[PDB]
Image (cartoon, rainbow over all chains, first blue to last red; front, side, top):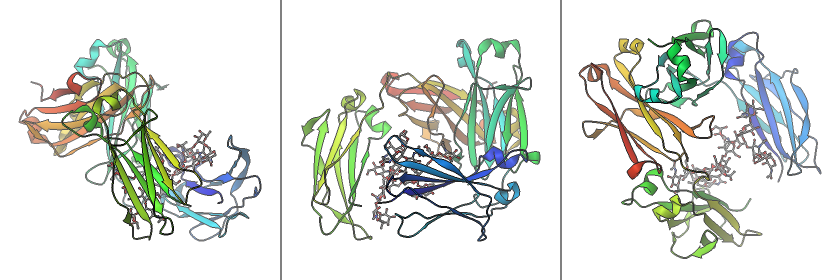
Length: 209
Length: 210
Ligand SMILES: *[C@@H]1O[C@H](CO[C@@H]2O[C@@H](C)[C@@H](O)[C@@H](O)[C@@H]2O)[C@@H](O[C@@H]2O[C@H](CO)[C@@H](O[C@@H]3O[C@H](CO[C@H]4O[C@H](CO)[C@@H](O)[C@H](O)[C@@H]4O[C@@H]4O[C@H](CO)[C@@H](O)[C@H](O)[C@H]4NC(C)=O)[C@@H](O)[C@H](O[C@H]4O[C@H](CO)[C@@H](O)[C@H](O)[C@@H]4O[C@@H]4O[C@H](CO)[C@@H](O)[C@H](O)[C@H]4NC(C)=O)[C@@H]3O)[C@H](O)[C@H]2NC(C)=O)[C@H](O)[C@H]1NC(C)=O
Ligand SMILES: *[C@@H]1O[C@H](CO[C@@H]2O[C@@H](C)[C@@H](O)[C@@H](O)[C@@H]2O)[C@@H](O[C@@H]2O[C@H](CO)[C@@H](O[C@@H]3O[C@H](CO[C@H]4O[C@H](CO)[C@@H](O)[C@H](O)[C@@H]4O[C@@H]4O[C@H](CO)[C@@H](O)[C@H](O)[C@H]4NC(C)=O)[C@@H](O)[C@H](O[C@H]4O[C@H](CO)[C@@H](O)[C@H](O)[C@@H]4O[C@@H]4O[C@H](CO)[C@@H](O)[C@H](O)[C@H]4NC(C)=O)[C@@H]3O)[C@H](O)[C@H]2NC(C)=O)[C@H](O)[C@H]1NC(C)=O
């Protein structure tokens, strides 16, 4: 009978590196032509702040609109658990919509990062799988990349975080490389970014031993 | 805001073992007191079927009804990609609600199952991680289990399927064992059930290599 509001956290990576800009994003769907104007109010722990930015809106292929406010956040505020309140008012709304988001609560825990070589069985293929196991980490916000010789390896896929039996999270990252690259003896690095790591970052190497 | 309909597919194990009973489940929620009568029609590839089993409505604590209908599917109908339509009629609807579900479309691909021992750096811990890599399967419906010496191992978690570059899926299963059980030389088995495996099953073993 009116729109819907959705609130999104910053990218894990954006909050760990001071050079990057972490953003909280407030998204309004089902905005129809007849009642086209949406507003936004923002709050960080009950205050209001004014540095949010409304980027102008897009017509959907179902003839409705998508409208987005974007608040930049302080890295340390996000990591310290401050609460970020989106407030949406619209003529079709009977009561304004508040929505809230925050970082997962609890003592952060350091990921353990382990590289595993391809299995003997796989070595009959033209391409092989380099595995990075990242386990024991909390909260689930994490970024994982691969490189070789300081250069980014982009042919990888990473699983979402999975809740482990001790309340921490784990994931696996799979890098796929030409078998010959693995045989010739190239070093591949899995890098992991996480708040509980020293300087928010660690790398583990993997090469043919 | 009238009733809504959720249509649930069978369990991956159920469609792969003839001994099991695969079901499609159509569930209707937010049925009102003022219009409580619900009708289901079921279709398999658009042809009506009449062997569903519908339970009588159950009132929820929020003063709405929930109504469930169960269709028993034949194993080979599901694997052959038949489509299952639940049609739901209620006098609070302006038109009946239809939902359709089937096995994801595309040519099935056989999973490659590879087992991977603990990192050397992990054998510092009291517990260690045995890994099962399952890749290159399609569709993503799969079941993964661990055992040793006949019996199920409880302490394992499996990732959801992840869409790979080539349009197939992969996942990993992690089994956590006490380091001594790995040092003692016990054999552990990752078994995988998928429609593109022979007898829909394969099992690969892992053990401390001498
Ligand atoms: C008219 O058109 C639009 C567009 O159609 C869409 O695009 C077209 C081209 C076609 O492809 C369509 O098939 C396609 O659907 C329709 O818009 C869709 O409408 C629904 C609402 O009805 C929205 O659903 C919400 O989605 C969010 C997740 O949103 C992210 O992921 C989407 C991809 O999966 C992506 O499209 C979104 O843009 C968004 O992406 C994120 O964006 C941020 C900011 O940009 C970015 O920083 C992120 O990186 C990015 N992430 C990505 C890309 O992965 C989902 O969270 C919502 O689910 C909650 O609410 C449900 C209730 O509807 C509920 O069932 C769920 O359980 C879930 O509930 C919450 O879960 C959490 C955690 O458990 C928690 O808060 C609570 O437990 C619970 N909260 C509750 C219950 O309130 C929700 O599903 C789509 O975003 C939207 N699509 C687009 C493109 O905007 C529209 O419906 C059409 N209108 C019609 C047909 O009438
Ligand atoms: C009034 O009460 C009733 C019952 O509530 C009950 O009583 C109240 C008082 C409280 O005590 C409640 O806590 C209690 O539960 C409420 O009914 C609920 O209504 C919601 C909708 O508002 C339904 O939500 C859907 O949930 C399903 C998941 O449902 C399974 O899992 C649930 C737990 O996770 C479990 O509770 C359910 O029973 C059900 O369990 C499965 O059951 C099948 C069949 O029996 C069984 O074989 C399975 O083994 C079993 N699984 C289990 C137990 O784990 C979820 O799938 C739905 O998500 C879709 O819809 C969203 C839009 O609504 C969308 O945003 C989501 O992304 C998702 O959308 C789909 O996305 C997929 C890909 O993700 C895609 O393929 C589809 O195209 C897409 N579909 C779309 C867009 O439409 C959804 O979240 C609850 O299940 C239902 N509860 C029950 C018990 O039936 C009612 O809302 C209350 N009314 C009020 C308060 O006004």
